[PDB]
Length: 207
Length: 206
Ligand SMILES: NC(=O)c1ccc[n+]([C@@H]2O[C@H](COP(=O)([O-])OP(=O)(O)OC[C@H]3O[C@@H](n4cnc5c(N)ncnc54)[C@H](OP(=O)(O)O)[C@@H]3O)[C@@H](O)[C@H]2O)c1
Ligand SMILES: NC(=O)c1ccc[n+]([C@@H]2O[C@H](COP(=O)([O-])OP(=O)(O)OC[C@H]3O[C@@H](n4cnc5c(N)ncnc54)[C@H](OP(=O)(O)O)[C@@H]3O)[C@@H](O)[C@H]2O)c1
Ligand SMILES: O=C(O)c1cc2ccccc2c(Cc2c(O)c(C(=O)O)cc3ccccc23)c1O
Ligand SMILES: O=C(O)c1cc2ccccc2c(Cc2c(O)c(C(=O)O)cc3ccccc23)c1O
Image (cartoon, rainbow over all chains, first blue to last red; front, top):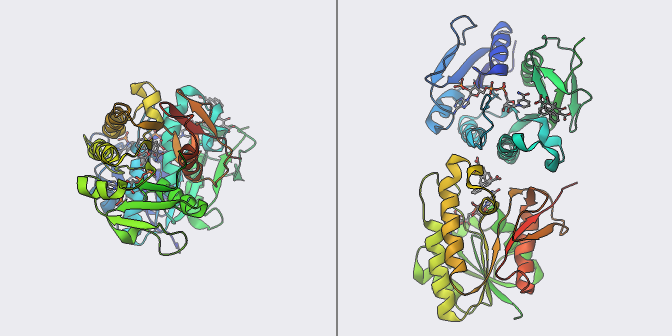
């Protein structure tokens, strides 16, 4: 019943990844995850269909994760770490190469609403990570793949609602999206082509 | 000082390709050193002279620099993650060839990381930045008229020709379009006001 049913999730162990994984498994997706050796999925949580242990910085590991999929969700990040990094942009380069080799077209990837900002107004403490989001978005935009650029504001702990606003190619009217709603939106992007080639800013007022 | 013939190194890269196109459309007689001719586009603006070879091969560089009025350097390694000397060894070959042929003017791209604290550099870019620093030193010590171009993030925005150029420091914006960056490399051929300076081109797109 699902045009998209086998998906790879990068960053499934992270804040948004964990609830995206849980929702995807409940929705009937056959999920493959790439996890780093020292940080596997928690014993409590939902179980994906396939687990690749490795690093998004290894093309071989990314290839093993992307092979055979219908689509890719990207929720990579550096947890609390604000240091200069290229893990997201280099990871995206590997994902793009693997998708082209394996005939996968659809990629839904999370960067940041700061990419819709006047670049000079981003807080300096956040500029190093934002710089790699900028690099990652460029890699994905230039790939020619069917790319939904998800650019959220603050990721919060509020509920799953499915009632959030999706603003196309600009900043939205609220400054938060719950991690659960952000994961819900990443999965919604698999069911439609309407956001392909756009930037999307999901946001909501939790009340 | 009027420049008609230029060599471009790195013409097949993202900045090189648009610099080449703009140079050809503006009337420059352009010589490129390319390792593979098939990487030059089949259509549109074509360079006047194509030397097939390697910036690591001194004979190939000498052949490219001979008879030019100025040199544009847009070399890069793209994927090197660990110590690498391709750019600095290329620049040594370029300097020796410019000296042997009486070519005075070189406009060379490194990166704005040379204007930031070293702790700003992502670990996997430290090797390429180290070699940018080595290449910059090679060019500054050469005695040639050298404009050091140190761009921030290189984007894909359309050509504007309206960017700002900050001298010997960082400017307000943190992006430059590859087209604007190539525009600025060519602007450096028409003036000596940037010689011996570091230049930081940047703009706000929109
Ligand atoms: N927090 C906010 O308010 C906010 C707002 C806007 C945008 N963002 C951006 O949204 C994105 C998702 O944020 P989040 O909080 O959900 O993510 P997160 O909690 O930081 O999780 C990052 C994910 O990436 C994985 N990862 C990191 N490096 C990896 C590597 N080399 N190889 C394989 N996997 C790797 C992590 O695995 P490990 O378990 O092994 O660490 C983890 O699963 C981030 O890019 C973030 O910057 C956040
Ligand atoms: N991307 C950014 O945002 C950014 C920011 C700051 C600074 N920079 C720096 O700006 C400079 C230009 O960047 P770019 O992205 O436009 O360059 P690029 O797309 O990576 O192209 C590099 C050029 O150098 C050539 N090259 C590499 N090794 C060579 C060799 N041995 N012999 C002859 N040619 C060789 C390449 O030829 P082939 O086609 O044969 O490979 C290519 O034409 C780089 O040094 C880069 O580090 C980039
Ligand atoms: O708690 C924080 O550290 C926090 C700090 C901020 C600093 C400046 C502007 C917005 C901030 C937001 C809300 C927010 C926004 O409002 C917007 C926007 O309106 O485009 C985009 C954002 C993108 C990423 C993260 C937050 C975003 C935060 O939560
Ligand atoms: O813009 C930046 O701040 C930036 C700064 C750099 C400074 C020194 C050397 C390379 C840099 C690249 C190269 C680069 C990369 O490093 C990556 C990556 O890390 O995946 C992807 C690229 C995609 C297209 C073109 C260049 C790419 C940048 O981009």
